[PDB]
Image: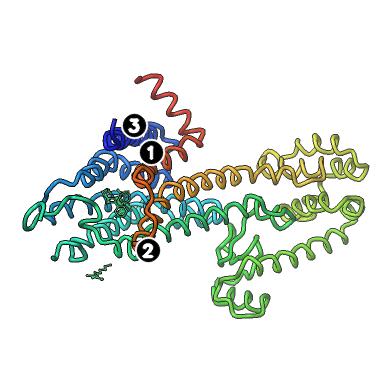
Amino acid sequence: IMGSSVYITVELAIAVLAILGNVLVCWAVWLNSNLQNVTNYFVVSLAAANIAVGVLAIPFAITISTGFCAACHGCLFIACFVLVLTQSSIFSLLAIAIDRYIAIRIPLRYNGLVTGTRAKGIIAICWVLSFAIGLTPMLGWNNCGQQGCGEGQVACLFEDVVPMNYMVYFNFFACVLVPLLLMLGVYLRIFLAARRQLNIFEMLRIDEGLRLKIYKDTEGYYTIGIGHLLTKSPSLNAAKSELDKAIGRNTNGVITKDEAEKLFNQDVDAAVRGILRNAKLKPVYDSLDAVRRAALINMVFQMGETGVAGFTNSLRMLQQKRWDEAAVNLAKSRWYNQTPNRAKRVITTFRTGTWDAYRSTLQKEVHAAKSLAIIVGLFALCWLPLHIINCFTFFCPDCSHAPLWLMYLAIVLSHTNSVVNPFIYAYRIREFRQTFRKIIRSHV
Ligand SMILES: CCNC(=O)[C@H]1O[C@@H](n2cnc3c(NCC(c4ccccc4)c4ccccc4)nc(C(=O)NCCNC(=O)NC4CCN(c5ccccn5)CC4)nc32)[C@H](O)[C@@H]1O
């Protein structure tokens, strides 16, 4: 069997695989309401782009490898679409990655930044850029201006109509490499967040939250950082002025993470001084190690000293280092009943003296980082070979040419992006995974 038959069969097989898997992803989000979030707005968009790739782009990419005689612009149109439909997938993928950057790195401002309306607005921007970039050759940047096929006709091959300086300068750098570098920067950032060094600052950030902008707290007072009240005055300018005084520089109501940590360490200093001046809490705070002290401070920040001093029985056990007995006793209060998540983490800290309960909470980010490593690795493996090949053909024509099977393999790889990248991310999600199981077992 000759090569062309192998290429078409493999290219067609990938088309079905790209269609089946991405139909599944949209099906799951369609019936399961736990998947009807804003993140999966982007996931479904990518699945749509990938169904079109399997339906239209792949048959086109095949077509523009047969070399039949065609009107130069009629063959140019075919080529540009496969460029459009594939651009649409790259940018759609980039939108998912960024949604995950904000969701993990900046969870408090996420729901505000990324809404259904903002999402559909971004998905729109993605397709508009895809058509603009993909159809640019039709504007005039084509190899058609100039025996074998006749006048006005050329042998319909990709390179015969699409210039190589468009594929290297415009298409590769601006629309393939940049997204990859962006997506890679996303992965590395989430990787450093998931594997971050833990401390009282990180503890309170997990329990209460970090805000690098000024915000009104539950009692309407302006606040910044981790619950650091600036002023009770209704004047935002006054809040901004108090902020500048504590920071030193002029902030405009915005600080860096490093500045919120200097505000926090000052609040911690304040909390300890109050603990040391409380006759009930002083003997216990002195008898604890650093990590358990941090958990005692966690309680002060939430209830104040008088509220902590009310735990006479639990405090007693802690001073005697009766960790287990102290824990079960603390599990009884209305503190636990009203904020069980936070109290359960604080108690585990008392019982173990480690950050365990607060490193367990980062496993969700660890899971997010590994899912993105797969996205960026598959993306680099699927797209770099083909575009590296173009770069060598454009900057060094006389160079040793790669064999036809490796060249066409790079094309196959570029189209395998549409079957792995969205689906693999979905399959790593328990909800998605269970929904896939439910639909295939029932309907199939
Ligand atoms: C969002 C981004 N989107 C994309 O990148 C999509 O665009 C398509 N694409 C992107 N570069 C593509 C591309 N480069 C051209 C490249 C090449 C050709 C074939 C296979 C891989 C790469 C090339 C290399 C060397 C010389 C010229 C072009 N050739 C095709 C595409 O069909 N070739 C099929 C039709 N041509 C051909 O048999 N020519 C042959 C290739 C072998 N001979 C050679 C070899 C060395 C030197 C000279 N003569 C004779 C011409 N398609 C491409 C593909 O669908 C991508 O998924």
Disc 3 to disc 2, C-alpha distance:
40 Å
The residue beneath circle 3 is: 20
Disc 3 to disc 1, C-alpha distance:
9 Å
The amino acid beneath tag 1 is Val
Quarter of the image with the N terminus in it: top left
Quick one: SS at disc 2? Answer: loop
Query: Decide: marks 3, 1 in contact (CB < 8 A)?
Result: no
The residue beneath circle 1 is: 419
Disc 1 to disc 2, C-alpha distance:
33 Å
The residue beneath circle 2 is: 396
Q: Is residue 382 left or right of residue 134?
A: right
| Residue nearest the observer in this picture, 135 or 293 | 135
Quarter of the image with the C terminus in it: top left
The amino acid beneath tag 2 is Cys
| Residue nearest the observer in this picture, 229 or 390 | 390
In the image, which is nearer the foreground, mark 1 or mark 2?
2
Task: Give whichever of discs 3 and 1 has the lower sequence position.
Answer: 3
Task: Give whichever of discs 1 and 2 has the lower sequence position.
Answer: 2
The amino acid beneath tag 3 is Leu
